[PDB]
Image (tube, rainbow, N blue to C red; front, side):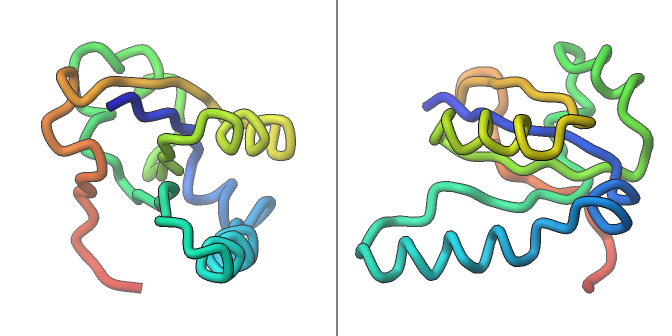
Length: 107
């Protein structure tokens, strides 16, 4: 499959543009429609360490987090709303575990 994503520092996603409610409202909407959740919060994304993402890893302040989704419009919407984030995409053949997180502590 193809995964679209926005990437930003956790600092930006906590002190300027928290996505907490965006996620919960969308999850509630999907539940009411009986739709399968296809968007996910991925802190310290494993994919960002792969060679093909070297440029974005250099540009994005760490620690970072990605919002990944198979719905491209949702990701484009996030970019329009947040602005100061990186955006991109990758396939299942390019990243073995698309949603893998390297986070080591629980919120």
